[PDB]
Image (cartoon, rainbow over all chains, first blue to last red):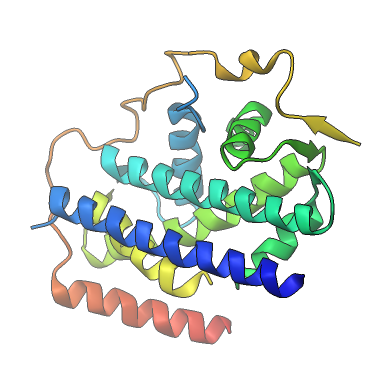
Length: 33
Length: 78
Length: 76
Length: 58
């Protein structure tokens, strides 16, 4: 139902935020002082 | 060549047009545009994945704007 | 300057396919352009704000990094 | 109804176009001049300003 849909999207968004954190860390390692 | 999503030149010109409304005579580092493009494409692809899940929950294969809107509300955007 | 048209219908289809979508309504194109527009407006506004506080006229990769960090905390 | 994304002619969406497949020089930084990283206090001042900006916008 809608609860399952909601849990799946929120779970994906958590993983996407971690992927973005990792991408921004790689950008810092390449471009930051 | 299924690595292609948004072409680089139109994306760059889009970014510069939007930025002009906030400050005049900006330049961009190449990697600043690249990072904006990576973030934008990751955002849209993920939104289409979530939109697709909304459509499927509605027993549909064709995603519609109401599916995008539902996904964004579940994601806490608006 | 109508550069939102650089987000072409093929580009939108390429993004949808990568997201696993199989069929789209015709109204998906304009909805996608609008969603990308606001996303970019929000991140670029923050990025240029960092640029201004750095007292320069070049948006750097790090300005964008901090704008994306901030967006992760405010977009949702 | 809708539009099938996987079907005849899908290859037309994946053409290579060198004139559009790279960033152009116009509007890009070409000298590595005046690109110093935000200092800690400049970042904090920007974020305080944006925090007030967001709170006022509601």
